[PDB]
Amino acid sequence: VDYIVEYDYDAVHDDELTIRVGEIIRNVKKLQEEGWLEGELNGRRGMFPDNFVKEIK
Image (cartoon, rainbow, N blue to C red; front, side):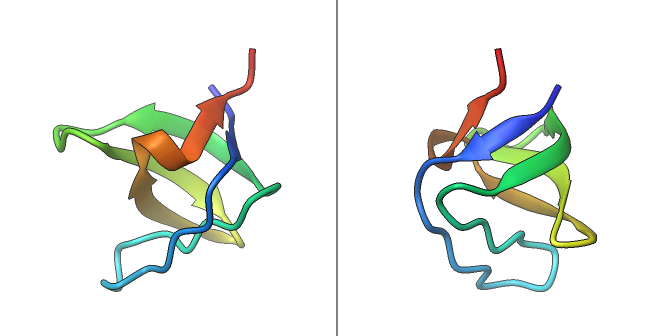
């Protein structure tokens, strides 16, 4: 399922996705890390905060 960024997040790590409010992340799935999701944003697959992106219902 896709997700929409509601809060700006700065990727501290290399596997972290730098999500910006208003962006749509392709195929956002839930990871084994509480508060971390996996999706293709900005042309890269990374991990971003769960409370920063809202599922596209």
